[PDB]
Image (cartoon, rainbow over all chains, first blue to last red):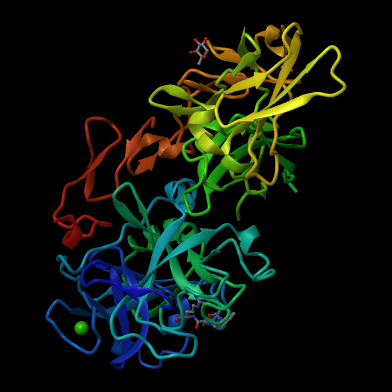
Length: 249
Length: 201
Length: 94
Ligand SMILES: *C[C@@](*)(O)[C@H](CCCNC(N)=[NH2+])NC(=O)[C@H](Cc1ccccc1)NC(=O)[C@H](N)Cc1ccccc1
Ligand SMILES: *[C@@H]1O[C@@H](C)[C@@H](O)[C@@H](O)[C@@H]1O
Ligand SMILES: [Ca+2]
């Protein structure tokens, strides 16, 4: 996260940390005790799917205070329409092998209905994005969870920054003055929108041209397009093999 | 090409009565308007209308010093990855709303002096279930210019006031006509109102 | 004065300008001529139909709640039915 602030311990309770071989990979969003939403591109290069780990209730990576809960990722589900090395359909649904326990420091973000997200949440100006990613473009990652308030754009207003590159499965958020943005390592993290006392999942940190670069915005995966797809899969019975390309729509 | 984007978005605003106007007349499509401040949520108005206008008064009077942006969505008729839209110019009500035509409330004469009182024009800014006056909103920012003359006046004379009354000197036996103009000297655009209807002794 | 047409509807008040007019409307009305009723607009596209969470048409007007919440008697509010409902932050809530 560039130009943000440390998220106070417990105030971003749905934030997930994904590790591979103990190494920092990406962020993610808990939406119930079993299921986590992340970015598809985070998994382009996994060699050993058995060493894939999700950590909840995390805050400081350099310390262990006892609120952390680790779970093995039993399944990574990705839209069949997603193509590794490209931007479109950058979303993944992760099944934890065992559910996490909900606590003051571990709580799911709500997955909204499509209509509600399209009609109401889409027009809430600001939303929070968070992660342990780079503090600057091509800089070092953060040890403490970082958070950032960013404004949302409809795509005609983003069109100039990314001509013919923003699909209906994306949206832009951030600042063209090059001061605040999500960044490498924040992928899969929530873009979370508050409405009437409750927080909802509206976006996923996906991609951008640099980080907080003048004249450009962060690009986020438009979660509203995947509500139906996500809910159908949360009902499907588990299958052998960690990775799974599920048809979209 | 199920819809066409609106265009020539224009703010029509007088005493804070603020209407957004656009083209074209709807063909097989309907419009929805949104308005916001630079950092506020979007508020929708005039849902699925076939009008080429939208009254946004109740939104802008909430804070007339804020700078507002509106946008008109085009929806295909009967079929209500986003809809086409167009952005309005930015609009700051306190600085841009047209001062309405003033009106002379009264004028009294005694001796070689005359009072000319301007009616305190009420605006569309509601507060406590009542409409605030033009001077309630602008205070010292607002002045009035009095034009006054007689049948034999080679030219109109001018007076000015920080309030709503003029106290001028006149010739004993002569009848004068009057006309007032509302001015906000600090403005850069729409600095002056139109002239008031003329009242004569 | 162009107000002689009495364009301002619904108990509105007309005020004459140079070559037009403006309508002062009652609190329940807006529009150039006070023609719009502010009450007759209970739809999901308009302020979420007054629902706290989910809304539905076609004609809220049927509000609903996310899992872990239930709809209250007012027919618009949602209340948690579990200890750790989604989208709420315990450390602040307390
Ligand atoms: C995977 C995530 O950690 C990371 C988040 C980047 C968010 N950036 C801003 N400014 N908010 N995403 C990436 O690193 C992607 C990876 C990628 C995705 C699709 C295709 C190829 C690579 N890379 C970027 O975001 C860079 N801007 C590079 C880039 C890739 C693709 C298109 C345009 C730029
Ligand atoms: C003019 O103003 C409107 C708002 C109403 O109060 C009318 O009764 C009045 O004459
Ligand atoms: Ca830790």
